[PDB]
Image (cartoon, rainbow, N blue to C red; front, top):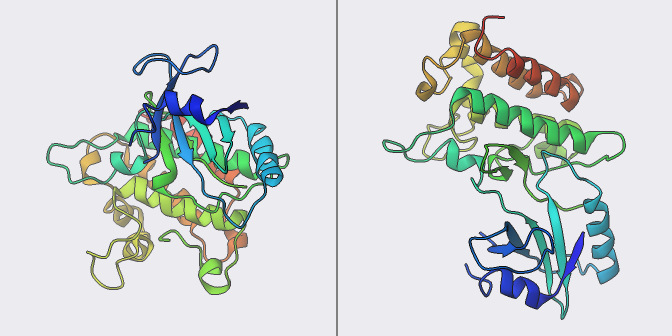
Length: 280
C-alpha cells in the first residue's frame, strides 16, 4: 500500500474536483498523470472518527492492505499529512448496484438475469472471504449501495472500516456478527431478484419492508415467481429464480443458527451460475 502526499492526490484528482473524488495515476509509478489516461482512482476523504490516533489508523490500513480479493475494492494507497486522512481505491467505473436495479426506467435498462446471478455470486464471494478463518471480518453494511461494479460488471464490496437490511437479532438486541451479515445478504438477494428496494416508504403499510411484502409470496414456487422482476421476462428458467429465492429465504431465517454460512450460499449461487441458461 503506497503512501501519498496531499499534493500528489491534489494533482491526480483535478484539484479535488467534485461521491468522493475522481483521480488519475500512471499505472507503473503511481504518480499523477493527465486526466483520461492511465489508472483511474477514487480518493475518499476521511474525518477522524472516535479520536483514532495516527498509529491506530496506519495499523488498520496495514491490515486492510493484506485483504486483497477479486471481490473487494482494491485499496491502492492512503494519505496522512496535516491532519489530512485520505484513502485511495481503484475506481469502480459502473458505480453501485443500485443504479443498475432500481432507477425510474422507461429509457433505463437494469442488469439482465445472468449478470444479476453473477453479481450476487461475486458479493457472496467477497463476504465469504471476509468471514473466512484467516480474516474474521464482519461487514455490517451489506447493502445494494455498497455493491460496486467495474467496467466489466464485476461486483465488489465497497470500502469498509475495521438500515433496511437489519437482522432481527440486531433490531431486538443490537447483535451483529456473521449470521447478521447473512440475513442482510438475503435481503440483498431479494432486491436483486425483484428489482425493488429493501425499504420503500411509498409502499403500503406492513409492506414498506421488502421481506414483509415478499413473505406471503415466498410460500410456493408459483407464488415465488410472482415477485421476479417483470423486466427479466423470458431471460431466466423458472427453477433458477426459484433457486435464488430459496437461497434468500434460507438466509432470511429468523433464528440466526438456521441461516447458512456464506461459503454455503457461495456454493449454491456458484452452481446456479455454472448451470445458467441450460436445463442442466
